[PDB]
Image (cartoon, coloured by chain):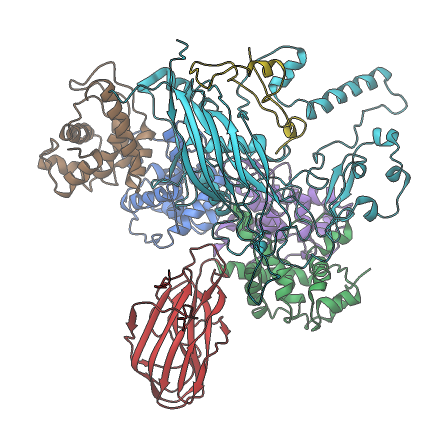
Chain colours: A cyan, B red, C green, D purple, E blue, F brown, G yellow
Amino acid sequence: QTGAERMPHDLSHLGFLAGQIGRLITISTTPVIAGDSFEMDAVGALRLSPLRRGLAIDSTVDIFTFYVPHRHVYGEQWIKFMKDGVNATPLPTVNTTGYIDHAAFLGTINPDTNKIPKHLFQGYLNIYNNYFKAPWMPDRTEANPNELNQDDARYGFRCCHLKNIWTAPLPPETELSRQMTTSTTSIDIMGLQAAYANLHTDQERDYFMQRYRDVISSFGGKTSYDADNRPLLVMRSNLWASGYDVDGTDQTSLGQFSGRVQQTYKHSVPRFFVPEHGTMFTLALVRFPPTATKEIQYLNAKGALTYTDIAGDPVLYGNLPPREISMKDVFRSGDSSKKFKIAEGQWYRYAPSYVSPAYHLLEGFPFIQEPPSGDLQERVLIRHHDYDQCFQSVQLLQWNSQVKFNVTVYRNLPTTRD
Amino acid sequence: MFQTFISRHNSNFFSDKLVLTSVTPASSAPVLQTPKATSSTLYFDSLTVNAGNGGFLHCIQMDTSVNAANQVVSVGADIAFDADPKFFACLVRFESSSVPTTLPTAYDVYPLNGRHDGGYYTVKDCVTIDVLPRTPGNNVYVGFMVWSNFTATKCRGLVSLNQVIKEIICLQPLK
Amino acid sequence: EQSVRFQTALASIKLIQASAVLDLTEDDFDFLTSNKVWIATDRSRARRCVEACVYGTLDFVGYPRFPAPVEFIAAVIAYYVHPVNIQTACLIMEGAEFTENIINGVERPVKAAELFAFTLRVRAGNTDVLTDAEENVRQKLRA
Amino acid sequence: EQSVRFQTALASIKLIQASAVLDLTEDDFDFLTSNKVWIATDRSRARRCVEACVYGTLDFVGYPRFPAPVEFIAAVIAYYVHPVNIQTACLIMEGAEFTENIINGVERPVKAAELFAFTLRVRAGNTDVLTDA
Amino acid sequence: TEQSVRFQTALASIKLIQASAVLDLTEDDFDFLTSNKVWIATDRSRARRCVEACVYGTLDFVGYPRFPAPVEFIAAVIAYYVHPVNIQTACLIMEGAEFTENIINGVERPVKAAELFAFTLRVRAGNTDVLTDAEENVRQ
Amino acid sequence: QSVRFQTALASIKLIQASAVLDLTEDDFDFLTSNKVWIATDRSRARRCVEACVYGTLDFVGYPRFPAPVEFIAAVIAYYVHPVNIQTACLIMEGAEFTENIINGVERPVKAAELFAFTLRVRAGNTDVLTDAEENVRQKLRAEGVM
Amino acid sequence: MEQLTKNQGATCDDKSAQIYARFDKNDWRIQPAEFYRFHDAEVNTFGYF
């Protein structure tokens, strides 16, 4: 009856939410049962608290949705759970620091008991670790929300900036040299070969595969290994939120202006079959693109320009391992001690974003004002703070959003008879 | 003419009678009465100021629950001393990890735009103080403080403070 | 817990006194320490100097900078910076974490208000030297 | 005293110093305890040494050596290493193959800022008047 | 202040401890336990014996068999009977020990040295008040 | 109209109503006494603990069945002296065959478990019971006890 | 059997595309155009969002 004989249930619901810039917050979670089709249509408005000065830059607003099967979370506790049936032991909960606000990142008001089922928490983690966070950053392993930061939990946890020379460098581990073990006076010609082979495999494998699923595919085989626990991406949409200004009219102002932002957005997910019981997270993330008051083009701040820098001589750029640059090679007042590997030639593949110096030292301007410091993580993850400068009330945090979630899911639960 | 609907300070609808009867001006200025939450109006018809060199003050405890570091604090007061002590007044901001009784060691002072006349003093002005605590364990307090090299005398009057963390409404008939 | 903070703050002043190197130029030094005021346009040289005192030897010799805790930066400021202008010197150093947080694995970046009230405290109980009590510094100047 | 956390480390040191000697050569102990500035080439020698003391302080008490306590690396860097190098000494220990900073499971290699935060705290209120002939 | 679940149980154990007067320590062990003297190598054996008795208490006085105890009960014990000079060894003595959670949920997750130390310390401080080291149980 | 385990236990302690459970004024003393339990009393330990367990159940309609670990813990937490909590948990561990209770249902009680729950109940953490009763409830509903 | 969409008329992948030709918002029965996979090239050809 494989069962097409299901009825549609109306799980649609308005949700007045709000959150913080630079941090991934969940917007709504609808628990799905197995064999459901779940279909969503989200419409609403995105705003930024009243800015200090007129509108200057806009922000990209990505809204996601993922499918996280309970199985990835209570592994084999869940398999017994379902086989066992009415007799299974009730499934773990996870604890939360006792404030009303603090399960915020999961889209629920922390229940009075300071408990939240594991799936809701482990999902978010299982997500952040797979889709945001640079592949090089360490997996976030946390048991219960008791282990979070007021910042990290009452708002969502911080994501990466937008991709760009100093925010998306090559993985810090990327080799700059492979040594072979040669004997004094002789190389083993046949050994060299094997040595390159081992590179080539490593190389691709590090960038071009990662998952078990990938290895096998390389042999031209297939396997449904779930245990990598990678949640599904279902939909994902992206807007650039802008608009308005509010010209002032009394004597003191006139030339003064605010910057009301309103972009309305629809974010839809089409009929998705739901393989097995599980929770469906949506999530939203707002980021202002980075733009520094102090970023300079490499070629203008590296110093004496040599042949491998301006030639663009593909041969070299072709056969030359990454180069270490330093924040000082890219920012005025950047820290030379702190370096990052960059593929040779990125200068010719990317261009800055110059913010004339008349702004640096002005207040309202969601720029970046001063090159981050700290290891490449603390440099790549957004600091939700340097935006408080361009707002007048962070009461409703940095972004409001009145939203209305149209969600119909066709499951077969019986009727209100019995 | 149209009625003004804006004011520098809004008092609490409920005023408290100072229970104490004598303060002794000091460097560790005493706190006239235990601090209340966000707003309170304190009135005393006979407070005997002993001789001393320092000041006494009146507290309100910053309700640090709304995410906003800088908030407006108000103070409105009318105090009359039997004698002219030649004192200066000011709003103070000191934090403490415990119910204060005396102005601690580290405190800050901000000018108010009141008017002095001999033994008198009236004011209604507001000032923006950073209400979140500068040091982790504390609670931050703001109060009105008079300070001088006191000679025994008495004073009458009221002194009310409020922390603008929310607005109050009032009938604007033309709406 | 403030006593521990204070304790660790003073303890760092002892370390600072064992300067092995300072990179500053006679002038940068007349800039870190003078009564002369720092206008907004100086905030960067300010940071170069304060930083030059926080990571000094590490730099001179070639080891990489690693993050210093707040209790240390407070010493550096209380000891080298003039009182007129500790505010900007703190405004420009906001961010670092207190040892406790580092230890506890909690992220607590520190904003201006904190660094200033803390350093101000340190300055008051740090008769360890004013700087005044050591002309020696000018020995370890630069080069 | 919040130093409730370091007392054993300090305890072992006292005993060690007075009662015995640790595996370090004569100029090595100089290296560790002296005013000499540690230049860049002195790394291996820096590890070689600070390691030495830590294993030592550890044996005496009765702790094993692989899970090596972050609090002992603190005491040693705190006591033997001259103040001119209490900073650089921390760096040289970052991610030493013996310690594990464990935070909720997460056995993460020790970052050099927590070593310095630990040492800058042991030193907070204790006797460290150490040079020795 | 907060102090939730794990800590709340740490407190609760301290209360059981005050009341469970009963131990299997001979006067001098109680000294050894509480001594401000450090513990060295050769001493270990008594250290085990003493700390252990301080945990399985009433079960040792009357000989019934043992019981693996939860990481919170173990820290209460160490917070209550061990000199701060010696909290650290008190723990390597009591390593694999699951927190109540894991015991309840079925997730065996043994705790090690550093972890119990962190916890004991946290327990130590929340009990500063209830810590009263009043030796009104110095018997048998 | 629904009185729950946990409230039953505190109620019965409040007004020491041994009568409600099936303890004699004397039994109640063993349970709640400041006396170390010796292995000669062991049997009366269980006798009484079980008596509190299956008693309150009967008091709150749960037709019998076995008792869930978490229920035994509550008993061992409200009715036993801090001197024996250890030995009490030791006395309930494992399936000693019973009175007339359902066979094919006896699943050995782990010991530590018993103590982990008693500490939590002894600490302000009532949810272990609450959650635990519902599971019980639902089992009993599919079974037709409602 | 199976379908995936675009990267970064309606959907894409040509074969998939064709099966998305079906539906009838009205047929409650399980449809093939249900199922899915999505691709934001940042990730596929990159690492994170």
Q: Choose top left, top right, bottom left or bottom right for residue C21.
A: bottom right
Report the label total: 0
Let me know if residue A87 appears in the view.
yes
Q: Residue at x 42, y 16 (%)?
A: G28
Q: Nearer the viewer, residue E29 or G44?
A: G44
Residue D94 shown left or right of residue A351 in the figure: left
Residue A92, percent across and down?
39, 29
Q: Nearer the viewer, residue G49 or F17?
A: G49
Residue G16 shown left or right of residue A152 in the figure: right
Let me know if residue B35 appears in the view.
no
Residue A228, percent across and down?
55, 22
Q: Choose top left, top right, bottom left or bottom right for residue G11.
A: top right
Q: Residue furthest top?
A: A1
Quadrant (top left, top right, bottom left, bottom right) of the C terminus of chain F:
top left
Q: Residue at x 48, y 26 (%)?
A: A68
Q: Nearer the viewer, residue D42 or B57?
A: B57
Residue F114, percent across and down?
30, 31
Residue A277, percent across and down?
42, 21
Quadrant (top left, top right, bottom left, bottom right) of the N terminus of chain F:
top left
Residue D4 shown left or right of residue F88 in the figure: right
Q: Choose top left, top right, bottom left or bottom right for residue C92.
A: bottom right
Residue A418 shown left or right of residue A325 in the figure: left
Q: Residue at x 25, y 29 (%)?
A: F133
Using the image, determine if residue E109 lies above or below residue F11. above
